[PDB]
Image: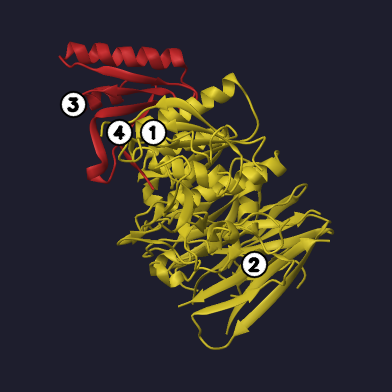
Amino acid sequence: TATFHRCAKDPWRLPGTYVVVLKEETHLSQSERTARRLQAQAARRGYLTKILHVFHGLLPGFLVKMSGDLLELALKLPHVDYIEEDSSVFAQ
Amino acid sequence: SIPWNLERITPPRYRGGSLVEVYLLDTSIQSDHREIEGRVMVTDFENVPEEASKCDSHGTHLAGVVSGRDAGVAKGASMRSLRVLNCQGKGTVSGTLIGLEFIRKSQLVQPVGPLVVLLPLAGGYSRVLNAACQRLARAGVVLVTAAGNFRDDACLYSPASAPEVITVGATNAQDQPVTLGTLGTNFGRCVDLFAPGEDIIGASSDCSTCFVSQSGTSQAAAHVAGIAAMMLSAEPELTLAELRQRLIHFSAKDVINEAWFPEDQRVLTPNLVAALPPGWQLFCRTVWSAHSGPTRMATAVARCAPDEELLSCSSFSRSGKRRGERMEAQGGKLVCRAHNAFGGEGVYAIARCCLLPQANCSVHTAPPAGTRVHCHQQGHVLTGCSSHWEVEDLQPNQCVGHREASIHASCCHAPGLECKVKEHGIPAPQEQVTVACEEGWTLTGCSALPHVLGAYAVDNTCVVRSRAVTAVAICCRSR
C-alpha cells in the first residue's frame, strides 16, 4: 500500500535523503520506534543511516539520510503511508 | 508619491494587521532595516542547504512589502521570519516542512490570534509539502504562496498546487501578467488570484534606509499576505473560505488580457487582481476540478469548503465528448461530479460554492423520460440545474434536460434570498454565448438549454461554449 514519490523535475531532486510519511494518526512514540527499526534493519544489511529529524505536529514521520537501495525495505515498515525523495525549492 | 502597486490595491472608494501575525519563510533578513525594524522578529530558525547584503536581499524586500513603514501593504504589521532559503535563494522541501512544523509548535506553546504564513518559494509538485500545507490550513492557519515564475501551470509546482493555500500570480502596472526574462508568472486553475508583482519598491538590504525595485510572484504573494492581514485584523473570526471569498469579491475583475496565457489555460485562470476592501451579501466562487483524464468511466469532482454550500454544478470538455454532471452527497456533503464520454480526453467538473448560512439545500433528480424536475416545496428556490446521461449520442423552480438524460435541480430553503433566471439565446452557431446577472445579484447557476462543449460561471457571467444556443443564468440576492 505504501508508495514512493520523487520530483518530476530531475535537476531539482536530492537523492540520498528521504521523507518517510506515516499514517495520519501515528503517534510520535511510534514514529520514533519506526525510525529506529529502519536503522536496525539497515545496519543488519550493512547500510549506515542517519535520522535527521522526527516530524510531529503536522505530519508524522521522519527525515532519513540513507541509500535509496533501502526504499523497498522502508516501504514495508509499520505505519508507512508514503516516502518522498527530498527536492529543491527556490525564491520566487 | 504612492508606489503604483499600493495604489493598485486601493479600491475605488477607500477610507492594520495588529492582532495578526505574519510568518515569512524565506532568506535571511536585515531586521534592523528602517522599513521593518521593531516590527519583524527573526526566529533564528534555520534549515538551508549548502551554497549579507546579497544573502538577505529577497527576504528583506518581502518583509518590507508586507509590513514596511513607507512602502508596505499592512504598515507596521507584526512578522516573524524563518530562514529556509540559503544565500542563493535555494532551499529544500524537508527544510520547508520543518519550518511549517516549527510554526505550528510555536502556536501550540504560545497561542496568539490569526496567523498568516507567507511562502514566497516554489519547487516541483510535492505530495508531502502539499499535505503539510493542507494540515496547517486545516489546523486554522492561513497560507499564502507564490504561483511560481516559470510561465507554466501552477498545478505542477508546490506549494502553489497545494489544496487550501492561497496561490498568487503576478501582474504589472498595465494589469497584465508579468514577464520575467523568457519566463514569467505561472497561471492555471491552482492560481487563486493575481496581485502587483513587477517593479515593486521595498526595503533593500544594501543599506538600512535603501530601497530597491523587485519583480516576481513572491512580491505578488506578499501583497496578498498584507491584504489578508488587514482583512483578518478587521474581521478576526473569518474562516479560510470566508477570507478567500472576500479576496475574490474585492478583486478587480476582467482586467487581464487572457491572450497572454496558453489557449487551454484561459478558462482555468481567474481574471482577478487583488485589492483591499472599500448587511449580509451572497458570495459565490467557481471551483474547477482537476481534469478527469481519458478513462472511459473517468469522473472529475469539484468540492466546496466545509462551511460553503454547493448551489450549482456544470462541466466542460474541450472536444465536447462528455456525459454531463450530477450533484451527489459525499460524506454528508454535496459535491459536483462530471462524467467523461467513452472516447473523450476527459472533463472538468465546475462547482459554484457559496456562503449561505441557515440554508437547507437539497437535490431533486429525475431519470430519462424532455426530462423535467422542479423544487416543488413552498419557500424553496432553485439555484442550479445539472444533467448527466449514459448514452453516447443525444417554469418557476424547474430544470429541463434532454429526454435521454437525467436532470438534477439544486433546491434551497432560504427565505432571505430572491432568485431570478436570465436567458440569452443566439441563433448563429457561435463559439460562445454569455448572459450576466445584474449588478447587485450573484450568479448561482450557469447552464445551456438542451453541440455544447460545456458551461461555466465567470464572476457573475454565465458562459456557454459551443463547438439556437441559449445560456441560462440563475441570479440570487439577499432580500
Q: Where does the C terminus of chain B fall, quadrant-wise?
A: bottom right
Q: Which chain is yellow?
A: B
In the picture of the structure, the residue carrying the numbered disc 3 is: A69
Q: Nearer the viewer, residue B208 or B77?
A: B208
In the picture of the structure, the residue carrying the numbered disc 2 is: B460
In the picture of the structure, the residue carrying the numbered disc 4 is: A86
Q: Mark 1 and mark 3: span between their CA atoms? A: 28 Å
Q: Which chain is red?
A: A
User: Which residue is the extreme one toward the bottom?
Assistant: B428
* Letter of the chain that mark 2 sits on in the rendering: B
* Circle 4 crowding by C-alpha within 10 Å: few under 14, some 14–19, many from 20: many
Are dots 1 and 4 on a single chain?
no
Is label 1 in a helix, a strand or a loop? loop
Q: Amino acid at mark 4?
A: Asp
Is label 3 in a helix, a strand or a loop? helix
Q: Position of residue B340 (x, y in %)?
A: 44, 61
Q: Position of residue B352 (x, y in %)?
A: 61, 58
Is label 2 in a helix, a strand or a loop? loop
Is the residue B364 above or below the residue B229 in the image?
below
In the picture of the structure, the residue carrying the numbered disc 1 is: B84
* Circle 3 crowding by C-alpha within 10 Å: few under 14, some 14–19, many from 20: few
Q: Position of residue B118 (x, y in %)?
A: 50, 41
* Letter of the chain that mark 1 sits on in the rendering: B
Relative placement, left or right, of B423 versus B464 is right
* Circle 1 crowding by C-alpha within 10 Å: few under 14, some 14–19, many from 20: many
